[PDB]
Image (cartoon, rainbow, N blue to C red; front, side):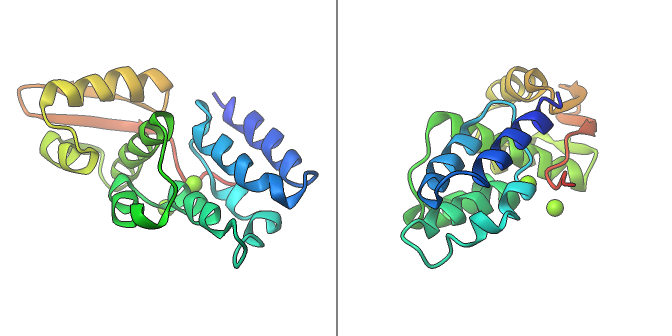
Length: 161
Ligand SMILES: [Mg+2]
Ligand SMILES: [Mg+2]
């Protein structure tokens, strides 16, 4: 954990040996993979960049989203992207927490709820503990009285060579 560096290795090796037709499926695989949170190195592959202009360009758009965007960016672009699976939705919400933690080491519950489309503090805390801390991508403290998440330790999305 990295575990991530290992999967990036396997994916880069496959992307640079497989037919270009296999790249869309590889992108769906990457964005569904339980241990993968950093997509920059994959996005930067010349193999992937060359999907632009092709029938699979929407999958490059999907990869760009997972590299750089938040759950909100997906909602904005949903009519021009494939529909996401539960695993992809979960991952984009986890990545959104990582983006927020990059900007601020104290995250108000109200901000988190808007960014993640979580309706209540229970659902929010459950997500932070049972999906984010569980995955090893953040370590911090929940302050129920102050309604905030103090997150000194968060995985970086722009983690790259
Ligand atoms: Mg990334
Ligand atoms: Mg960044």
